[PDB]
Length: 408
Ligand SMILES: C=C1C[C@@]23CC[C@H]4[C@@](C)(CCC[C@@]4(C)C(=O)O[C@@H]4O[C@H](CO)[C@@H](O)[C@H](O)[C@H]4O)[C@@H]2CC[C@]1(O)C3
Ligand SMILES: O=c1ccn([C@@H]2O[C@H](COP(=O)(O)OP(=O)(O)O)[C@@H](O)[C@H]2O)c(=O)[nH]1
Image 1 (tube, rainbow, N blue to C red):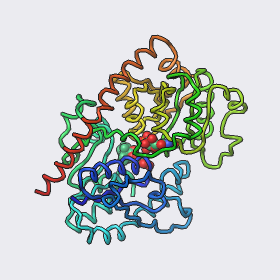
Image 2: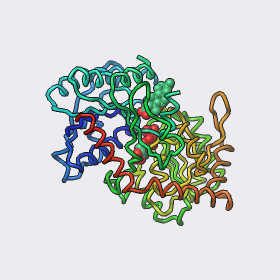
Image 3: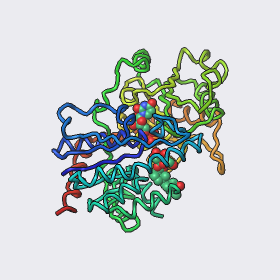
Image 4: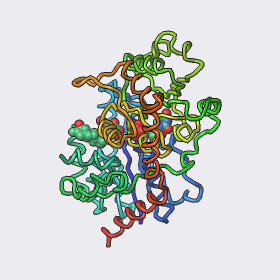
C-alpha cells in the first residue's frame, strides 16, 4: 500500500510517526511523510534500506506576520505566548491547498492524519482516499474523550475520518480496550504500544549528558524531563529546582527555558553551584532514549507525555509524575493505578505544586527503602509488557491488515 502520514507540527507527534513510517516500509509498504521543511531537517535519518520507501514531502509553512521564519513546531512556538500559538495555527491551516494538490496525484491507499488535520481529512474525502485519524495515546485517554477551537478542529477531523488509531493494547490496558468499539461512530483500532526500536533515533552516545551518567552509580540518577513543548513558567521552574535539591538525589534535568527568561534568572540563585557535585541541568535537546537506556538512571521525573511514559517503562523506570496538560493527567492516573509511579501533590483548582511536594514524591519513589523497592518491582512488571518487542510488531502487522481489509 501507499500510506500518506501527516503528523502534527510537534516532536511528540513527528517522532512516533517517523517510527511508524519505517515500520510500514519494513513490511514493504511505501510512505509519504508530509510535514514542513525545518521539522523534517530535525528528524532522525531513515535507515538506508528504507530510503526509497519513505518519501519526505516538504510543504513550506505560509508566512504570517508575527510568526518568525523557522518557527514550525510546538518546540519553537511557546505555549506561554498564546498570540504566537494562534499565528502558528493559521500558518498550519494554510497547508490545506498544497496538501490537497499533493494528495490528488499521490495514488494513496490511505491517509493517516493527526488530531487537528481537519483540512487533510477534507482532502481525503475530495480524492476518495480512506482516512485514519491518529489519537496515539492510551485507551484510558480515548475512553475519557468519548465520555477555530482545538475541540472543534478535533471534532471535524474525526467526523471526516473512517478510523481512529490508538497507541496501546489489551495487555497494557485490560480494563479499557475490550470496552471500546467506536469514538463518535468511528471504529477504534490499537496499533500496540509501538515502543521506539533500539537506535532508530541515531542519538549521540558521546553526548556530555551520557558521559556524565557513565560516572554515576547504578540506578542513582533521577532523570527529569517534561517533553518537547509543555510550558513551565520561571516560578514553577524554581519550585521544581528547589524540590530536586531538597530530595538530595543525583539528577540529570533536560529543561526548556520559559520565553524571555535569561540563563541568569532561569534557576534559583546558587542552585547550580550547590548541586554541581550531584546534578546536571541541560537547557538543550538531550538524547532521551540513550539516557533512559543508561544503567545510572533509576526514577524518571516525567510530565507523562505518552512517548515519555512508554520510553520510561520500556526500561523499567518508576515514574515521579508532574502532568501539565492534555493527555498527561489521564496518563499519570493510569500509571499510578498500576503502582509504578506517584504524582507530585497538586493544589485542587489551579493545579499548583511546590518544592516540598516535589521533594516528597522523589523521596517516596527513589529514596525510602521500602516504597522505592515496591515502585521498582511494579515498574519491572510493566516493562515486561511495554518492552515485549515481538508483541508490538504483531500489533503493527494487525494494524496494516486492518488498513488492507477496508480496501478489500
Ligand atoms: C475538550 C478537550 C479534550 C482534549 C484532550 C486532550 C487532547 C485534545 C487537545 C485533542 C488532541 C489530543 C490531546 C490528547 C492533546 O492534548 O493533544 C495535545 O494538544 C496540544 C494543544 O493543546 C498540542 O500542542 C500537543 O502537541 C498535542 O499533543 C482534546 C481537545 C481539546 C480539549 O480541551 C483537550
Ligand atoms: O530533550 C528531549 C525532550 C524530548 N525528547 C523526546 O521527545 C518526545 C516527547 O514526547 P512526549 O509524548 O513525551 O511529550 P510532548 O513533547 O508531546 O509533550 C519523546 O519521544 C522524547 O524521547 C528528547 O528526545 N529529548
